[PDB]
Length: 192
Length: 192
DNA sequence: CGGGCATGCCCG
DNA sequence: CGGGCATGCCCG
Ligand SMILES: *C[C@@H]1C(=O)C2CCN1CC2
Ligand SMILES: *C[C@@H]1C(=O)C2CCN1CC2
Ligand SMILES: *C[C@@H]1C(=O)C2CCN1CC2
Ligand SMILES: *C[C@@H]1C(=O)C2CCN1CC2
Ligand SMILES: *C[C@H]1C(=O)C2CCN1CC2
Ligand SMILES: *C[C@H]1C(=O)C2CCN1CC2
Ligand SMILES: [Zn+2]
Ligand SMILES: [Zn+2]
Image (cartoon, rainbow over the protein chains, first blue to last red):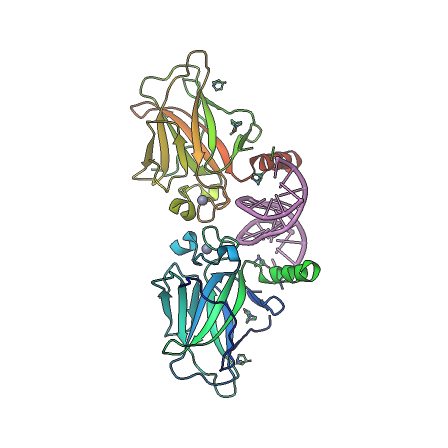
């Protein structure tokens, strides 16, 4: 009955976790302390998928944004009117690049947007699979996120629709990821 | 042949001038030193029309915005996509309130927007006529003015289309007119 | 209300 | 590139 998707971590029977590359006032940088990606608009944000056990054939990887703060959690996250007017429907915040099987979904009941690609196991000798996401507005965009923090929820789903795993990370899309990560980490240490 | 309207002051044979009320970190405030109105979005910006000689019956008062800086002067000033989506067409920046004969014009050749009302002479004992303009975006709106200063051009035109007078003033539509007027006047004194 | 943060962007 | 302005908005 809820129109708010779960954000609860569920690493599940396949041992699903996300990973991030190591990254200066930079196009993206991930804070482990904050579980938060800082990235620039319309630029690559790589996300690694790690599993302990191989998901079945036909597994899918879905990404969806939700507002982090309770007061905004019921509002659908969408592209702002300016960037909408500038495969992906123009209203979608999150895109996937570099994939020939990307599907964009608008839920008929919840109106939430999501982007899905097939799960592919790592190549031999590799421990993870990387997806290249793109966020098409800044967190600050007027008429869109409007300075409200979001979480990205990554779910691993079988072809039948069973939830196999779920993880999430906060995102700030901003002009100066390195500056803003340093500011937020310092604020955590000083006032958190 | 130009699609850029003239901004040259022409006080003309009727002695046409504009005047502004005297106005604190306020909903509007006018700087004589800068010839610049500082006002808030979607709030009244009164403009006084002064003449030495009475214009003929059927005279009209037109207002049009143009970008002040040479680099932007050929671009039409429009409402940003966010405020457009929130009588006046939604794309028009400048509205007139309190008038039952307001006309909104989109020029078929230049694409410029303007808003026109009939000229009315002052009531007996008064020396000026006041029009209540409204600016429907901040100067800073992304996808609209985008922090570029504008001028408002006020023309007095007869019913036949003859230009009787023209005046202009700079406008900054902003959250804190009193703060910003003080900052700009101090910068003029210190660095201008 | 005024002080001061915010954050995309400017300038060196 | 990094320092620091910008400017709608937050908090007291
Ligand atoms: C987004 C950034 C980059 O461009 C590389 C890969 C992931 N992060 C860290 C370095
Ligand atoms: C999971 C692995 C790694 O740790 C490196 C970068 C991404 N994949 C391929 C090699
Ligand atoms: C816009 C402001 C106001 O609200 C009054 C009239 C004109 N200015 C100065 C005071
Ligand atoms: C021009 C006149 C004035 O100076 C005051 C305010 C506006 N009109 C009416 C009275
Ligand atoms: C964050 C800051 C930088 O370091 C350059 C890119 C974006 N912004 C302006 C210059
Ligand atoms: C300009 C500043 C003020 O003084 C109040 C109105 C708008 N802004 C926030 C509070
Ligand atoms: Zn946007
Ligand atoms: Zn606007």
